[PDB]
Image (cartoon, grey):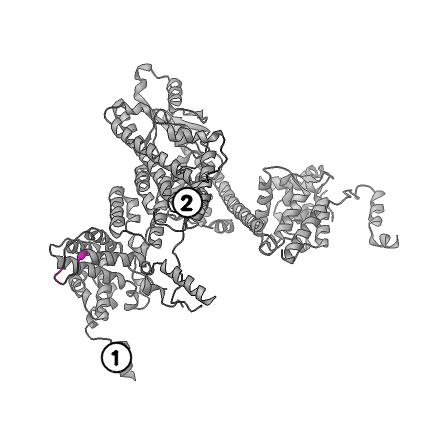
Amino acid sequence: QLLSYNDLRHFQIIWNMVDDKREGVIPTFRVKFLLRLLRGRLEVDLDKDKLLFKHMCYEMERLHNGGDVTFHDVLSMLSYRSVDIRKSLQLEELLAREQLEYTIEEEVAKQTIRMWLKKCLKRIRAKQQQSCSIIHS
Amino acid sequence: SGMLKYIRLQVMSLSPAPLSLLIKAAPILTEEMYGDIQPAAWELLLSMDEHMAGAAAAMFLLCAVKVPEAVSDMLMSEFHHPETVQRLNAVLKFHTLWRFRYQVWPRMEEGAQQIFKIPPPSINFTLPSPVLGMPSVPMFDPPWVPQCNLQQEEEKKRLGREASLITAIPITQEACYEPPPQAVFPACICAAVLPIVHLMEDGEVREDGVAVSAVAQQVLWNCLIEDPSTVLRHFLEKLTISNRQDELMYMLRKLLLNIGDFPAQTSHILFNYLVGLIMYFVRTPCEWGMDAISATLTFLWEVVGYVEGLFFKDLKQTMKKEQCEVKLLVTASMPGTKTLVVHGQNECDIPTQLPVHEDTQFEALLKECLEFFNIPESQSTHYFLMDKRWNLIHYNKTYVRDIYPFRRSVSPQLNLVHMHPEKGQELIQKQVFTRKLEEVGRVLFLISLTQKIPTAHKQSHVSMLQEDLLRLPSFPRSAIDAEFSLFSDPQAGKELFGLDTLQKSLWIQLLEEMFLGMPSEFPWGDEIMLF
Amino acid sequence: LTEEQIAEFKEAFSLFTKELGTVMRSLGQNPTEAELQDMINEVDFPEFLTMMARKMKDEIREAFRVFDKISAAELRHVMTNLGEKLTDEEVDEMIREIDGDGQVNYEEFVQMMT
Amino acid sequence: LTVDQRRWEDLKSRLKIAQPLHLPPRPDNDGFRAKMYDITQHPFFKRTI
């Protein structure tokens, strides 16, 4: 039910394969390339866990606003998400985790809506300026 | 067996055979026969036989659904009938209709919901999530639950039992075992509530000693305890589509001052509905929005009078989650908009974006907009800034951050409109009067909220209130500052002064009430002065 | 290997100047053969990913998984709070852009995506 | 604390003491060091040592 030594070794190998240097930190945008390459017990199914994968991506993106994240941060995130938090956490920590994940879910949903707005607003940004030109003309 | 079973199940009595048939063939009935049959159903509502009463109630409900105008007119005529007997009979008929509302659908052809359409209730309100307060107080020793040093236990049980209120629940609706039922109570019957509210004050006595007021009070008390939402639905939804706040608040105040109490569930539902109404009105700008919010706040402080599980922490957390919390409590901190966008008198002209600090009068913004738009000094007094969306005309000396506390990505949109100075002054007077009344309502609401809390938790509540009050950025200015410039106005100055004296008195009362709650050895610094 | 490039490129640069086009054809793309050299100048797995992920960067499931509630009030609130600056007047069009029942089905919006 | 919570805390501490893998080298570029690395990491070499 918990992270095993083999899982930690595999994750370290994958990190060393995606982290070209030995700086111990990678740009946040690269971190998704970590999650989907991870294999074995920690593998995530893109055909069934799309929502979970996006949730993890934005959770680590929100932890530091556009900042670079260290190995320990991603390790701890996977460690938390690999356990039944309701059983292995204290009351206050469980409440904090639940609130954080709920906020992340809502935030990512409205971020998809933000992309939808990007498209729709780009479409609608023509009529008003055309009317502006007509008024000027 | 066959004949006996049939007579015992399918034919309870021969009298209600015809009426019941009309229920079975309700969809085929034309609008004319509904009106033709309405008088018989209305008259047969008081029959001693239960089957006849139920059949008549169902038929009348279907008639009301199909022809609301006729039923509404008949009800209004009966409630305003000259003789006492007719009014008392109408009240009894309403009670019978209310208690027979759950037995309509079974009486007609099976699966008639698809062939017969009842419009779903229309509500634009989003009730606060989570629910603000306890839905009800459980009885200490319910005699209708199977579950469950001896003498002490019995003494404790008796003492706790004395403190409860058995008459405040729908007794017969709670004992029944719980192993769906649909209620058909069209909105045109709920209108009958208001006549009963008026009748509560009718002292006429029938020859057998029954008084109209007593029967009306009993019926409405039973209705409120059984299902608060069903009775208080046709009013809450209706107010959204029309600007009749005054009448509805008058009616609710009469209800409060005639029943003399509100059971926990009724006050809970009313408070949640009113809060949701305020949230919707602030949410969706409308022509009569601010007036509706002021009217609702003017009465909310009485609804809060009877609520059990309302605590400061839960209310603050949930209302902040809704994020439109600055219109209810006074201990609300919200960073205001950093920038403001304003259009000129003409259309499609180059707008302007201006900065906003925390101590900016509208006078400076008006001056900057006036000078930037190349306007002669002679007509300076003829131009005023106003919000078209919310239809607000703005006072010169009100802070930007106070009127637009929302720190969203979207800055408020203003317009520089030209009009006669007298009309502008009158509109400004009206709007500032309404806003000051709203502020008084908020203070009263907080007073009522903090005047009913278990004495054990009162110290914690008062300490929390003091902390939030101290951490608010501009509290002494908010509670002390007044719009002096408008007092000199002869037409409306007197009213504003008379309402401001009341506001100041309520503020003094709030601080004194808060002071007494805290301990007698609180470590005070210089910040005491701020209070 | 799978449709997503992450499992494509561990093999694309470990199993094999021109043969790698065979993996590109899995995506249905046939760029110029000379261009196969252009990205090879990056020689590196992470660099190849960084380039071609944004290259490919340059539907109803999400719509149904965002309907987690959506009347005028909720739409207005979520819409003003969404993010980057946007004049609220255009939201007036957004509420009107069919059934008029006060509810929105994201499937119709996905249909209207273009 | 439940023993599961104790295990959770133990795993947290283990992750705290955890460190990224030491060797990042690329053993594919050269034709001499490449085979040397390939044979070096073979488990049988460690077993014989």
What is the span of residues highlighted in magenta in the rendered image?
B205-212
Task: Give amino acid for label 1.
Answer: Ile
* Closer-to-camera residue (B399/B60): B399
The answer to which image quadrant residue B151 occupies is bottom left
State which quarter of the image contains the N terminus of chain D: bottom right
Dot 1: element: helix
The answer to which image quadrant residue D21 occupies is top right
Quick check: B272 above or below B466?
below
Q: Name the residue under label 1.
A: B7
Q: Is B198 one of the magenta-colored residues?
A: no
- Crowding at dot 2, Cα within 10 Å, few <14 / some 14-19 / many 20+, comes out as some
Q: Residue at x 41, y 32 (%)?
A: B404
Separation of disc 2 and disc 1 at Cα? 55 Å
- Find residue A92 and name its label: none
**Extreme residue toward the right, this view:** D49
Q: Is B207 one of the magenta-colored residues?
A: yes
Quick check: B155 above or below C15?
below
| Total count of labels | 2
* Closer-to-camera residue (B28/B65): B65
* Closer-to-camera residue (A99/B421): A99
* Closer-to-camera residue (B47/B108): B47
For residue C99, say whether it is visible.
no
Residue B353: percent from left, percent from top: 44, 25
Task: Give amino acid for label 2.
Answer: Glu
For residue B352, say whether it is visible.
yes
Q: Name the residue under label 2.
A: C74
Q: Which residue is drawn at 27% across and 51% down?
A: B260
Residue B88 as seen in the image, left or right of residue B354: left
